[PDB]
Length: 260
Ligand SMILES: [K+]
Ligand SMILES: [K+]
Ligand SMILES: [K+]
Ligand SMILES: [K+]
Ligand SMILES: [Mg+2]
Ligand SMILES: [Mg+2]
Image (cartoon, rainbow, N blue to C red; front, side, top):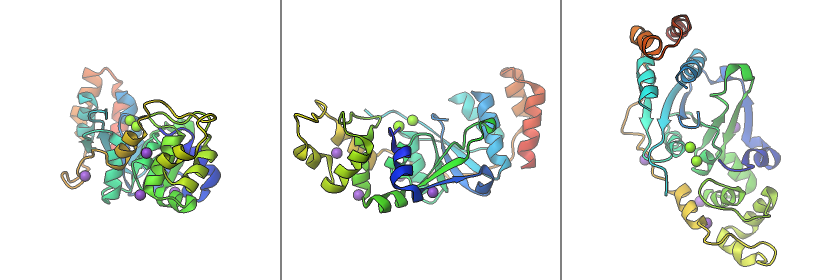
């Protein structure tokens, strides 16, 4: 994730966020961060997306920087999936950049840091929760803050990312001000009072910066994404016979999947 990024954007770049009903994404292809998003839950969430005309492609994590059952269910449902070489949401970003999908879907705000033009949050949320889709457009963030992607990456590092520490005591609004004035973390460190704001020791901000800018990602052109009809009998057999889920529950969902 990126700590505080969503709230910060709502505060200082509100035009970059839109809250939309799930119904409004009819016909959209969406790349889903499979790890952030168990079999019955995937079954139901995917059906809910398909009922609304959304065509999801699930992207699975590769090796981190430094599931066979789920894939079986997706194949039987007619839902495509991809193995990312590394972080799934970075490959989701690549699929958006390449025009293969409309948006990336994940709760991980660092999908924007990896450069995704569009990020949709809460798509995988259960229908009961009543959460509207939270949709971010990266270009609007950069335009509102007057930053380029490199500067945005350093801001996200200062906010707090998965891959390195942040500067203790530097708040989100303050981090924006520092990035706007100084452009890079290297310059910020020259200008900060070490007596007031000491930086972490052995700080890996350069390494994290390079990871966000040049992540290892799949090639969107290698696999043509396809959505097809489910294998209903095999689906029942696997989910009910092997995985002990309710035959009535599965049949109801399968019926809905075909009807959509
Ligand atoms: K938006
Ligand atoms: K840049
Ligand atoms: K950096
Ligand atoms: K690529
Ligand atoms: Mg991450
Ligand atoms: Mg992840």
